[PDB]
Length: 235
Image 1 (cartoon, rainbow, N blue to C red):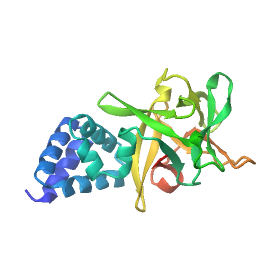
Image 2: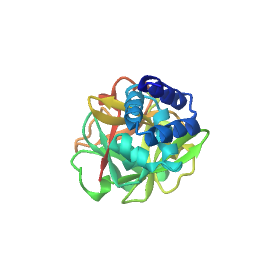
Image 3: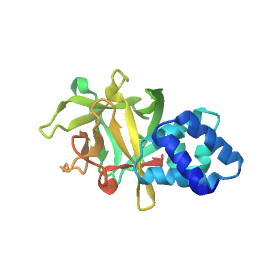
Image 4: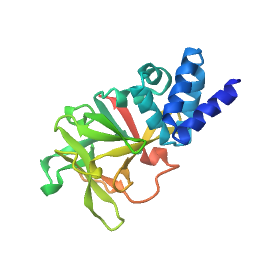
């Protein structure tokens, strides 16, 4: 069976979401010393923005096979599933995600992309994952505040929702799924809110200080990694 067919039979199981199966074929391939099949499948998923590549990294993660994720996927999947201190870097603008100091009403702390601050402990986040409905989701916890990223209910008139940090994961509002993308050679993520299915972005209106408010965005993002997606970087 040429690596042709193997790749496509690994890519298949992944996109119709047969995660159990993709795991097996990936263990075999791996044992059979054909890792380059796995790598290449993965880079193909990430190219084609296949959300299902998060779920295949997660099942490898829980199915004995951590070595496959650290081995054969871009370093981010390790940063994510290993729960490391990371920062969330917006491609468009290059600002790092953070939380305001004071609390905005019952809605929590305001999430923005801070204008100056790229190394302070305030820009530290972890990913914390679950499995529901044959899909992986993340809690996004600011390190300094022990508060989760969340999307508030009220919209502006575009239908955009505001992002804050709250003390609990109460609702589907505080849970996120990711979609991988390339832009050049960087690996990026569109980060959607489970409840509204809107993409985490930074505002186009810019505050005098340099910060941009972060929003759950009501419109298309796909095809514009450089404008929309995020960089996971070790804190």
